[PDB]
Image (cartoon, rainbow, N blue to C red):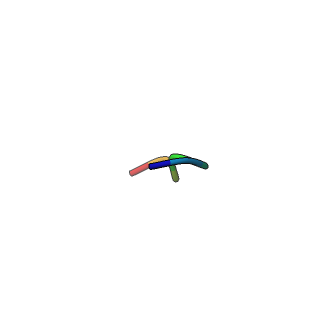
Amino acid sequence: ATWLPPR
C-alpha cells in the first residue's frame, strides 16, 4: 500500500 499512518 502507501501512506502508512502512525499508530
Rendered location of residue 4, percent (x, y): 51, 46
Q: Is residue 4 left or right of residue 7?
A: right
Q: Nearer the viewer, residue 2 or 7?
A: 2
Image position, residue 7 (x, y; %): 38, 51
Question: With 4 as the anchor, is 7 left or right in this view?
Answer: left
Numbered disc total? 0
Residue depicted at 49% across the width and 47% down the height: 6
Residue sticking out furthest to the right = 3
Of residues 2 and 6, the one nearer the viewer is 2
Which residue appears farthest toward the front when viewing the image?
1
User: In this image, 5 relative to 7: left or right?
Assistant: right
Q: Position of residue 1 (x, y in %)?
A: 44, 49
Residue sitting nearer the eye, 5 or 2: 2
Residue 2's x, y, as percent? Answer: 55, 47
Given residues 5 and 3, the one toward you in this image is 3
